[PDB]
Image (cartoon, rainbow, N blue to C red; front, side, top):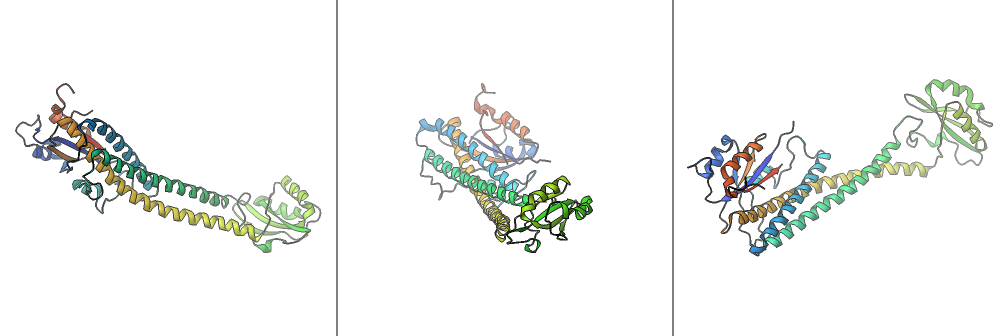
Length: 364
């Protein structure tokens, strides 16, 4: 079960009243009449931004639409990453707290960050500044995610080496130097994975699989559900014959040339891959969480700007607007929207039955 957590940002002229409820006060209508009083409606406070030029409003509206959509896409990705790491949930509660309060509490009290994004800057310059910072945070998250994924690649490769039965699995964490004839110019050791059913066949036959097998040298050094792994000591010059003969008997010789260096480096691969994945996972969780918060705050600063520009374009100046954020109950978004349109769609002109007034839907 997926439970929608949708919000509507709406702006109206200060003196606009719902056509469907003549003689109602607009503010009480929102609380008591809209969808039978079942929405949670809050004031949404927006600064009176510095319009650089009346002529650039339409271009700012277009840019704000683009940036609103871009940051929304970025936040969606960050959330996906956190979900992939079980740092947040899917069907419900798909956010993190903002400023140590739940998203809905943050949204019921939105305040423009006047010390961060100074209100003496034009709309044009605020867009640039907020858009650039948000883009950088997105690039930062993407870079660390790519690095983490690359670490996961090395970890998965190292882990894969220790999987499978004794016919395929790496033997480096199984064998000991005592299992081998080491540092001989003429003698060596072959490891053979033998299907458990053929264990006796091997024990009976190995001493004659080639010339110069050391008699009685075979021992069982490991076993699993399907296989026994034997060592066998024999002359280096006879290893090809032994290997070919063993394979013809359905035994599986396992190439293994024992050295401290080889074993050490194979151990160091797995250890180092695990430590690297661990470190990058922690780095990624921390960065994705801090980025989520800063990006979400920035997203709502962009929405504030967008709502202001649109309200100026659609309702004119001076900027006397009644602005609200609505928490819509699950399964009631389509109805809330239609009730709002019936009540206030006149603002768009009778010919326009795009929303007919300043209204944005945010899917959280």
